[PDB]
Length: 402
Ligand SMILES: [Ca+2]
Ligand SMILES: [Zn+2]
Image (tube, rainbow, N blue to C red; front, side, top):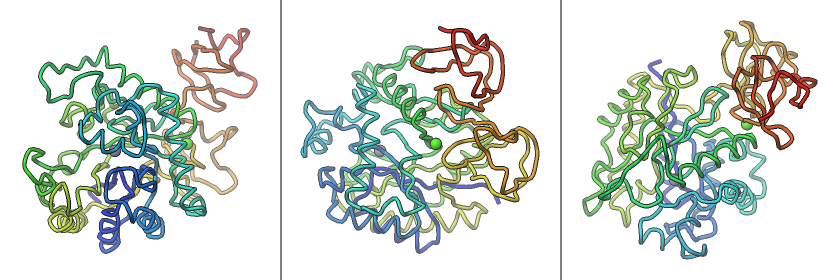
């Protein structure tokens, strides 16, 4: 195959999600939906009376449901959050301004998301494709927490003052905005609580946000496949436009990113309504893009498989990454997986390579790594694989207390 495409849809569930899902099912592909549950509450300022129907359809159809936070951080767009905040933020267009403020409260919106999803769909945890407690994507931000050595931040994603297109706008990646730093803190909180976060390589969006009906200008299937072609193995998160969509320190050539393209788009771009004739004009583009991509040799997959799940009988090379029960592991040696020898906190064949920064058992630590343990920070003096009796302490010379 040519490569793997991960179609990811942000900001549902809304009425428009249903026709998108129907096209996906027509074309026999699965996608990943990064949902904001405030649409279930009817306060997200979209056509969303069928939001619960949409959520159920996504899950019953086998699509992955992942975590985009309860309210898309819109509580940070207004003075006091309420049923009208979505409309208010849409009126000012200030979504990307002061988007992240208090990292604790902002990170709690991912937990809130889980509570509201489970409120509206009480048996949601019985779907294997419900993954919202393990996979997240931050509003506005091409941020990544995938493995211990695969992390990146959107250093111009959000602003303290001006939007990227406004006069006087400047981004200093060496001295980023307070909003950007708060988002980084949110990423780190989520990682320490077991989340992976993923950004995107290409964003399927209007070619012209300036016309009357912007959605109509969504890239045609044929040239959008060209964009995907151009992104395959070219470190797209560092070169993507606009500037607020960049992940400047993305680790180009990192092994898990090879031969893969993550597409970001939004089901609201596939709706006949306030943004244009999205359903009539753009659902056919979605259909033909999927068909063209398959015929060009791509396959479609979902974000639960971006890091491949550990599988009995698979051959692994030293250095390979897998997921096992939500945790990333890296292969210590080349071997063939057997059912009774799975990755674990004590496995000789695997070390934990989660993107967390709390001290963790069975991690291959490097000199200079910083860990947190019992509320204290420590710096690793020498590379080693952590084990239970080598936890940080003031007497453990593997570490220096900071
Ligand atoms: Ca995890
Ligand atoms: Zn979003």
